């Protein structure tokens, strides 16, 4: 067998081995230098088309030779020396002079059309040509370039739900011509979304098939029934002809996929909402968080999709209302546009209302999102939650959104000696796992719930449990701006009477 | 160094961990494997406590030097056992045969699911013919029958296990390497390696000697500890040191490279397997003070069952042999000892009643008529450990 | 053309021909001793990196010379004699003995 370098070469120099070459020409020279057999030459020698004899010669070859020597000699003697010269050049820009391989022997090989070909076949979706999140798509691509050297690695593009992670992977693999061709040879992009225990195996059933040749999809067996040890062994075998192959695992929920990815020594991009699935991997884990859209980015995003920019003061405010409600959320923002047909600042404000008196369901629409409304998504983020954590979250509704508030002020509504740090532990798990909360260490340990993460709970928790938590708070009321609420003034949560009376 | 990785991956060997590499052990494993590539068939037992780190060391011992694979042995087959059912020892070897099967004719794989043991065995070796010097890591054996099969199949085996006595199944010579609790110095190294702050003051080191005492050198629970200290400050490190006394191992249970949320999920099994009578012996050890070397007679007091109670000692040996739950010591006088990881679990697991009943059952026999073991003039007072007894 | 011995030498002494050498230095001396062509020197003379000029000098050279003379008789003159000495030593531990 060879390896990723020697097989990446047979793959890079493939546009060429198709235009002029023939495995019949090399069979005699290789039955000889002791690499193949008399069935090998039979199998590659009786093939109707040449792309067959070529794909079998390159498959059979990668297994048989201790190295990439005899092939060069063959190309040279066969008057196809313009070939054996290219491959010997490539093998040299690796051992002696490293680095130089991508700029010199790999860059000219770039081909956007091939990228399409490669994108489509790796089941990569189309990217958002309209608005592009500059910062992020860039930083993704960067951290992927840094790692094409690495043998196996996890990249976690983790964020809120509908926060826009999956779209960025579409763009980060679609802008530059480097990631595919230069840094990685092929792409495999598979959506997970697995919840059952059979899901982590079913996933890897469709990887193997993402790998397998166009030939022998006919022969695809009842692989449906075969052990995990075998699908795994069966994959890492069919993985020899996958040099520098990247893996996008769009939407991982189960840390069992991450465990398989690391037994299979894979190179993975990973979109997920729950970040802790990475604790499954003892390895080079690097992270990129898809934050809520900054206030300025929201403007850009609106303009990009024909949305009218403010003038009057209570019009930039009409729009700060949407941005506050949406709290910079790609998915629900998009649902907004599709649903602000009139475009008027007026009908834009109509909706700003519908959002307070109907939650996310006021703007649920047909969108490029698989989901009618962000509530359909978050459903899951909440089911997965530790039974005890499901409780903690459920009571957060009472807290006023968009306000930085102390741990003790939370200890009042949340279920469970004298030290309630346990509240904080739950609230961390809570931001780590769907980014539902928001942690902020100093000046003092305080969390905060945004609005999208709120009107979710508003029209979703037991109409009773809202009112019970409110009363359970007013009891602890007495007990004993850019400024956090002081401990001399907790007795009055009354500052937010405004944002409390609306219950 | 690129051919190994091909061979490691195909033999289903896990990835290599480098952050912390137990020098001594990975070395001694590799050594004793080199000595044997000559041998025709042999057992190497890398035994130890649950999550003692055995399986990780086999990952490293076959991943450091490239001699073991290529030079000493041609190929690798690493299979996780964990078999409890009686069909498990056959199912194991089914995959083994499948592993022997090349990529070609994994399509033709038959309903081998239904075919006698004599045939899977005869068939396996039929495929084995095309296999020279193939080591067989059997990660996590808990059934002696697996070994028995390994010896009918004249195999070359590395074996990670918790129960050491499964080796009595093999008449052939079996060498052994025990994965001990992490020494006090190794614990430091392990902490630093994973960004853990080293003491600058006595209190600081004591906060850390508390973790090492609680963890008692258990990597798995140590790892769960780290993953659970976001602040990491000596402070939040001590917070946890508490959580451990008032919640057992469940205070630090976390998502870890371990298949297990907490060491209690592992030990569960080690305890089920136990002789029905031995399950009893273990269950009462909770009353005993941990990390204290204590006499056999002082144990004869809580443990169930003429006038010679050596039977207590026999159970306590089986007890250290089988998951390394107890500690064994011959002289100055025959004494055992229970560590804290092996204790906190019991403390927060065994019937809440049976704890208090064993404590009283000790008092009845209590009255009877430091680097120093407790003398027979002073057993009447287990009161030295009143401290570590009042906390019940 | 050369052969396996004379080409195995240019390959064995390769870790060295990379640390200190330059094909531009030899082009004039070889267009001369009749072993190159004015396209040959063009091809090796306009190359951005030296590992390029070196890989082309060693490829082009192995085809053109009847022997490995006019390259020992060059590292000598170029103050790179620590090179032409290594290669002449190698050609001798094969020319004067029938065993390997
Ligand atoms: N850059 C963008 N341009 C246009 N729409 C976007 C963009 N980013 C996100 N969206 C909106 O979000 C929807 C898809 O969101 P995306 O899949 O990118 O988020 P996500 O983090 O993958 O959510 P999930 O984790 O649930 O897959 C699109 O239909 C679109 O409405
Ligand atoms: N050298 C090490 N470096 C880092 N972590 C380790 C090491 N050794 C053990 N661990 C911890 O233990 C976990 C796995 O333990 P390991 O499998 O090595 O023990 P084990 O003896 O196999 O237990 P079992 O017999 O139950 O398989 C890892 O997830 C890690 O948390
Ligand atoms: Mg998506
Ligand atoms: Mg293990």
Image: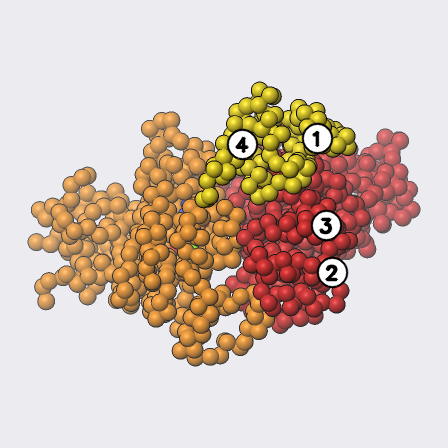
Chain colours: A red, B orange, C yellow
Mark 2 and mark 1: Cα distance apart in space: 44 Å
Q: How far apart are marks 3 and 4 (CA)?
A: 31 Å
Q: Which of marks 4 and 2 is in front?
A: 4
- Mark 4, other Cα within 10 Å: few <14 / some 14–19 / many ≥20: many
Q: Residue A51 got which mark? A: 2
Which is in the foreground here, disc 2 or disc 1?
A: 1
Q: In which quarter of the image is ligand 4?
A: bottom left
Q: Name the residue under label 4.
A: C87
Q: In this view, does A14 lie to the left or right of A199?
A: right
Residue B137 versus residue A95: which sits nearer the camera? A95
Q: Marks 4/2: CA distance?
A: 45 Å
The answer to whether the residue labelled 2 contacts the one labelled 3, judged by CB atoms less than 8 Å apart, is no
Dot 1: chain letter: C
Q: Where is residue B330 in the image (x, y as percent from the top left)?
A: 16, 51
Secondary structure state at the residue bearing disc 3: loop
Q: Which residue is drawn at 9% across and 64% down?
A: B307
Dot 3 and dot 4 within a common chain: no
């Amino acid at each position: 067998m060879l390896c990723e370098i020697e097989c990446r070469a047979l793959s890079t120099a493939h546009t060429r081995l198709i235009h002029d070459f023939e495995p019949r020409d090399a069979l005699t020279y290789l039955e000889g230098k002791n690499i193949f057999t008399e069935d090998h030459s039979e199998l590659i020698s009786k093939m109707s088309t040449r792309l067959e004899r070529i794909a079998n010669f390159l498959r059979i070859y990668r297994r048989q030779a201790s190295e990439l020597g005899p092939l060069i000699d063959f190309f040279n003697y066969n008057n196809q020396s313009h070939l054996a010269d290219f491959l010997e050049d490539y093998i040299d820009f690796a051992i002696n002079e490293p680095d130089l391989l991508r700029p010199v022997v790999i860059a000219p090989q770039f081909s956007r059309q091939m990228l399409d070909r490669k994108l489509l076949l790796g089941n990569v979706p189309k990217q958002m040509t309209c608005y592009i999140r500059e910062y992020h798509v860039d930083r993704v691509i960067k951290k992927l370039d840094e790692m094409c050297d690495l043998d196996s690695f996890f990249l976690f593009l983790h964020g809120r739900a509908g926060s826009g992670k999956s779209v960025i992977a579409s763009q980060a693999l679609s802008k530059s011509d480097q990631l595919i061709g230069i840094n990685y040879d092929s792409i495999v992009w598979l959506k997970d979304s697995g919840t059952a225990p059979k899901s982590t195996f079913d996933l890897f059933t469709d990887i193997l098939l993402m790998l397998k040749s166009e030939d022998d999809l006919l022969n695809f067996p009842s692989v449906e029934h075969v052990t995990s040890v075998v699908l795994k062994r069966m994959i890492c075998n069919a993985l020899i002809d996958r040099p520098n192959t990247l893996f996008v695992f769009d939407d991982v929920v189960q840390e069992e996929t991450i465990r398989w990815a690391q037994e299979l020594r894979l190179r993975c991009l990973v979109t997920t909402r729950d970040v802790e699935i990475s604790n499954a991997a003892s390895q080079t884990c690097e992270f990129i968080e898809v934050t809520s859209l900054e206030i300025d980015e929201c403007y850009d995003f609106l303009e990009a999709y024909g949305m009218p920019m403010p003038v009057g003061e209570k019009e930039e405010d009409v729009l700060n209302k949407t941005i506050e409600l949406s709290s910079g959320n790609p998915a629900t923002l998009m649902m907004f546009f599709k649903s602000c047909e009139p475009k008027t600042f007026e009908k834009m404000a109509q909706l700003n209302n519908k959002l307070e008196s109907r939650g996310l369901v006021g703007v649920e629409c047909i969108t490029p999102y698989s989901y009618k409304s962000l509530a359909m998504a978050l459903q899951r983020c909440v089911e997965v939650l530790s039974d005890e954590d499901r409780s903690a979250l459920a009571f957060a509704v009472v807290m006023p959104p968009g306000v930085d508030i102390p741990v003790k002020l939370w200890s009042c509504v949340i279920p469970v000696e004298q030290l309630d740090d346990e509240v904080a532990d739950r609230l961390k798990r809570l931001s780590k796992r769907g980014a539902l909360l928001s942690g902020k260490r100093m000046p003092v340990l305080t969390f905060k719930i945004d609005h999208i993460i709120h009107m979710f709970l508003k029209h979703v928790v037991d109409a009773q449990t809202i009112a019970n938590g409110i009363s359970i708070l007013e009891q602890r009321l007495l007990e004993i701006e850019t400024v956090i609420r002081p401990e001399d003034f907790p007795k009055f949560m009354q500052l937010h009477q405004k944002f409390y009376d609306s219950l």
